[PDB]
Image 1 (cartoon, rainbow over the protein chains, first blue to last red):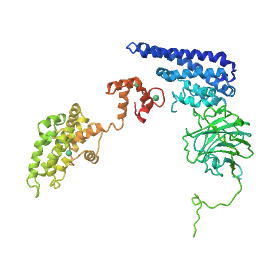
Image 2 (cartoon, each protein chain N blue to C red):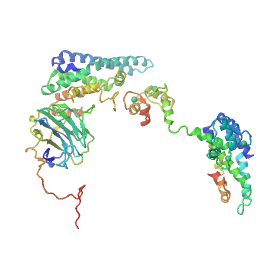
Image 3 (cartoon, protein in one colour):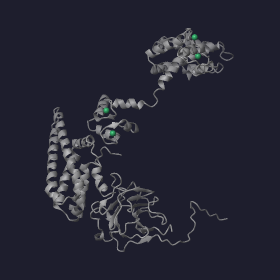
Image 4 (cartoon, each protein chain N blue to C red):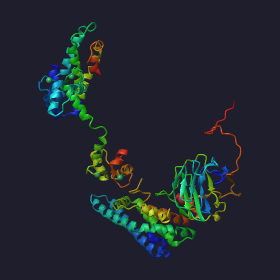
Length: 176
Length: 194
Length: 97
Length: 149
Ligand SMILES: [Ca+2]
Ligand SMILES: [Ca+2]
Ligand SMILES: [Ca+2]
Ligand SMILES: [Ca+2]
């Protein structure tokens, strides 16, 4: 995390976009397996429910190995992306958005992420307050949905997505 | 003297907001004792901002937020830093940003104050100490704001004076002693007509 | 006889057996016969009355079923409690309470 | 009631203890009888306190302790041991394994034994309400302050 503060904008396209895309398709592949299990209810579905739990657990490990680096990179470059629209930044919003949608829809995804944080003692708070400590500035300390990196990254990338839409599209957004 | 130390600037009471989301900027030309935030219309001119319940201000000299006392919040500012004061009367929260970056307390709290009652309403306010210079931008010209697009535009906040012809009238605390009637509810002084 | 019964472990181990034997009914009938005679001018054999009343009070505290059984005679105890004020110690009013 | 507080074995044990005090067998405990057993245990009290420790449990005031009063003393001693620790046993009912946390599976186990049934999803609803820390387990401290799971 300390070394990401000097990262150049080229890392967004060269490294971050290909990496998150691999995570995005992996997330879609696992949830595709998860919905396959539920459509055919069976006593064997339990033998295989553990398989997708293992797939979700390893997936959550990969997300937490990249999102803390991504979150810090977004914070130091979100101002430039909003000042001048960037196609790559908009593409990254779709990737993190689809992962969030997968996380919100899938019940096991939330469970495995919560298990990963508590069992590995992931702070999930220093990842969001390191910049404040870098600048020389209880309730859910073990785990909280508000401090989840899957949803924290999206909220930091949300202004990028809203920047694409014109103000005339506000009515269409409400309808959708 | 005790009174010619802090000069408080606030908008006129006719601009009181009781709903919606509003945004304005305060530029710290100097780095000394200056406070900026939101205050209620009944703000008292001889009391430091945030020392009572009538103001929610951020002290950028040493990184503190003031409301009925002081508690650490954010980081101290530098010369030329712009503080973006944001109030959300739909969520009853107040957010302070420094150069487009949201200030945070010693926790994950992204908002300086929470569960604030609307009541009479709120007004933009700032106070300057001895030898302090600050620039207040209420956003009459949206292009003049330096960090509204970076943080505040996409969140649904509007400049405090987005659609206004004349500049917002401001009132300041004048340190000229004047004779006023003794209040009937003065805590220490009582006058009886015999 | 009351003292020996209250000194017996069976009296406390098997409250249902005591209820089946009608022990509380027999003690109550003896008490009211003494209270019935001389119901207004003078109560004689006071020690017997307070022994029966104390026995019934401990009988109620053994189990709720015993307490319920004595509750069925609440009106019977109350009508004999008008003159029980004369005797001091354990009285039919105390048994009702 | 004595039946609730005491079992048949305990009543038998108390009767043997009462007979140990009552060497005469008349059915009453006198001061000398009470004093004798105290000397056997080492204490050498005076008759002033010896009477006081009799009057403290003597109900009818006759000056002697009989078996009904002796049982009433022991019944109170068994009852007043537990004052507010009833939540500890309630916690252990949900806590099958024996540690200091209530797991969702453990909450499933007790809910399975009870009449109401859960669809394996609302079990997470009340456990997250009780668990403030968010670790997925409700500890003893979280249970006493607010009980939902
Ligand atoms: Ca004896
Ligand atoms: Ca006695
Ligand atoms: Ca457990
Ligand atoms: Ca917990």
